[PDB]
Amino acid sequence: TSDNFFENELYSNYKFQGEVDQSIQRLSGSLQEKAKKVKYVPTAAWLAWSGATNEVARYLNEAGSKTVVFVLYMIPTRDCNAGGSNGGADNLSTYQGYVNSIYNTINQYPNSRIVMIIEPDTIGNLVTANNANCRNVHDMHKQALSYAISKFGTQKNVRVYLDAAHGGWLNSSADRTAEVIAEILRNAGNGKIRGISTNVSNYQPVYSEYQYHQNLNRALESRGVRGMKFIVDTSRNGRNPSSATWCNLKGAGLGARPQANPDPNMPLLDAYVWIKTPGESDSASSADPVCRNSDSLQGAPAAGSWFHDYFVMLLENANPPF
Ligand SMILES: [N+]
Ligand SMILES: [N+]
Ligand SMILES: [N+]
Ligand SMILES: [N+]
Image (tube, rainbow, N blue to C red; front, side, top):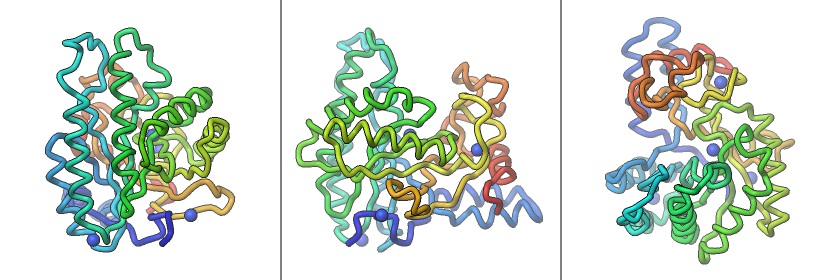
């Protein structure tokens, strides 16, 4: 009945549970006691490779009436220089195949309550990345996002949040961000979004994120996109970030636990949500220059892999404390 699906018990999933089990087995006493409390904190499930189409059903079977939070992260290319040939065969079509599969599976669970978060990092780059090369990729990314919203955004058992980066990236560009978003919604058919997600995989404070939500909302209203609500990723934002370094930031902490309507002074904010999986690596330390910054925790395994020493740091730095 409520359109804020976070006003429901949230699903805690077996993958996260198993990843924290990994850390727990490596810890003793007090730290281990704190890990056992982090094990059951609900975290989003990412759909992040071709076979994740086959992972949906098990999550929905195990969640029952509890709210499932998925992150759609399947756009087949994020990198420019296509550039051909020419420069895709054929990304949009294959993406539409992934979305249909996932939507078709979701229609089978009418009684589930699903939150779908659409494609982190895409809107940021559409606003700020410069696109001689990328123009072909840019156009395909907008069509990917419209197609995803046009499907999930008509499912009664789903509430869709479109990702829109973070204040640190787009608060000084809120108007162009709103312009981009409105264009995508215009081509999304009858698909409707509940709102916008921010701070995914990033470490900005709730308070500055909410000032971003206020500015983006004002700009979205100006473009005729009214009524939007917001969720913010509190997985790693217990401590203010020392720098703009994205990749396995040192001195991060776990942030506020997932909670619906957490402050009546932030009426636009539907929920704090752990969207990024805390303790999974951002990238291997050798995979990007940013991962060699002096404030990026070295020794990281590949993106998505459990990073035990980073998880420990998050637990130690948790704000509020476990
Ligand atoms: N709400
Ligand atoms: N269900
Ligand atoms: N985000
Ligand atoms: N943090």
